[PDB]
Length: 183
Ligand SMILES: CNc1cc(F)cc2c1[nH]c1nc(Oc3cnc(C)nc3)nc(N3C[C@@H]4[C@@H](N)[C@@H]4C3)c12
Ligand SMILES: [Zn+2]
Ligand SMILES: [Zn+2]
Ligand SMILES: [Zn+2]
Image 1 (cartoon, rainbow, N blue to C red):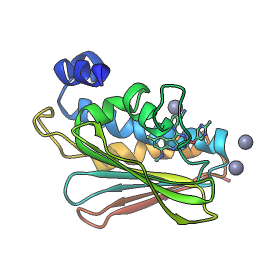
Image 2 (image 1 turned 120 degrees about the vertical axis):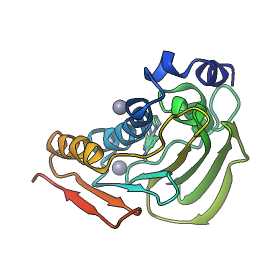
Image 3 (image 1 turned 30 degrees about the vertical axis):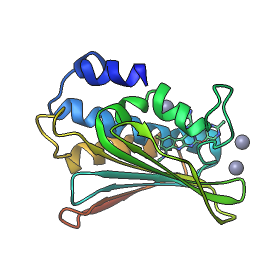
Image 4 (image 1 turned 135 degrees about the vertical axis):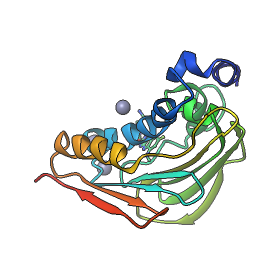
């Protein structure tokens, strides 16, 4: 967790600012990982929800973040959320939730002020994919309001670059919705 403490100590080092543009770094990172699964993991659908409480949910129907034991002796999902680019989202969020469908099972993990909980094996499923929820820390960010039009423009770009990918955007704050798809 030394990397995460470094991000929390100097957030602007990692996301440039703690204003609106800094806040949107977090949604870009999680969206990017979901969209990466379209080229790499045969995902057909990405969904982004702007939650009523300021949180964000991103989901894909890709391979699912690996849950197998990493060489560092913890589930790979914990390595991802502490070491890869998306670990900045974990560092600067009060909490994150991860749901994974892979290897014939649902899996659930939580991060509480970036600290991993205990990976839980849930029910059997033939489905695959990943859901990440995160709640930006208002102690870090001078604004916590995501901009629907800013997010829409990024998702339209990502649909155009990933032909056949459906991207759904839902604003739970006001009900606005958009679906992006290029054949
Ligand atoms: C909402 N969707 C979402 C959010 C998120 F924060 C991270 C991921 C994600 N979907 C993901 N899907 C996968 O499937 C993979 C990738 N590679 C292999 C070998 N197996 C399965 N892997 C993921 N990750 C591990 C590593 C990627 N290069 C990063 C992130 C993410
Ligand atoms: Zn990427
Ligand atoms: Zn493949
Ligand atoms: Zn596949």
